Image (tube, rainbow, N blue to C red):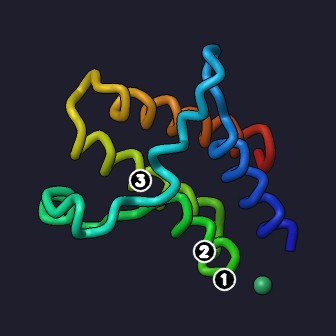
Amino acid sequence: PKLTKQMNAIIDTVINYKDSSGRQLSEVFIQLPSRKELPEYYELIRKPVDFKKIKERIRNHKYRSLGDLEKDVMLLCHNAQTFNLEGSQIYEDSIVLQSVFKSARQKIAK
Ligand SMILES: [Zn+2]
């Protein structure tokens, strides 16, 4: 009950986070492109995930702990760093989002 509350609070801090420029870094990660526009993603990436899917898993009670949630958030970021070039905007945003998740988790449910 407060597990669900915690998870939404943690994921909402990640989703809503903005850099010093005002840009919402999560935008690109909310929903993957489908197989059609981007076929190359699904051939290289073995376990695709997006924040909509993570939100679905929280809502439907699929995460047993904060650790299980963290595993999916770390996968999202890892997939982004696999698909995109080191130093690209998307790669670097995923790095910051990893760290946003960890801080939010420490702040919210130490
Ligand atoms: Zn429910």
Q: Nearer the viewer, residue 83 or 65?
A: 83
- Dot 2 amino acid type: Glu
- 15 left or right of 40 in image: right
3 or 2: tag closer to the N-terminus? 2
Residue annotated with mark 1: 60
- 21 left or right of 8 in image: left
Ligand 1 lies under 8 Å from the Cβ of mark 1: yes
Spatial CA span between label 2 and label 1: 6 Å
Q: Indicate the position of residue 43 as horizontal and vertical percent values.
A: 13, 64
- 103 left or right of 75 in image: right
Density class for disc 1 (Cα within 10 Å; few <14, some 14-19, many ≥20) is few
**Residue at horizontal 65%, vertical 22%?**
22
- Dot 1 amino acid type: Asn
Spatial CA span between label 3 and label 2: 14 Å
Q: Given contact means CB atoms under 8 Å apart, are the residues at marks 3 and 2 in contact?
A: no
Residue 41 falls in image quadrant: bottom left
| Vertical relation: 28 (above or below) 32 | above
Q: Residue furthest front?
A: 37
Q: Residue furthest right?
A: 2
Residue annotated with mark 2: 56
**Image quadrant occupied by the C terminus:** top right
Q: Given contact means CB atoms under 8 Å apart, are the residues at marks 2 and 1 in contact?
A: yes
